[PDB]
Length: 21
Length: 30
Image (cartoon, rainbow over all chains, first blue to last red; front, side, top):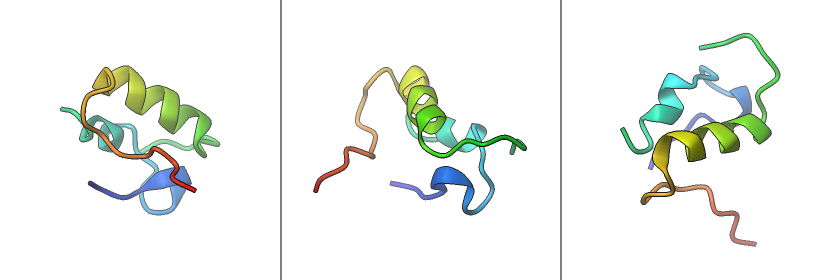
């Protein structure tokens, strides 16, 4: 899996897309 | 990248709205 959470690195939503797409 | 107060509530509702509950991670095992 990948990292990012709460707004620790680049608080992105496009990054949350990486989860399935 | 946004400038809001996104600390879990929204990263959860958002990741789940995009995945459709297909093989992703963040299932707090305590």
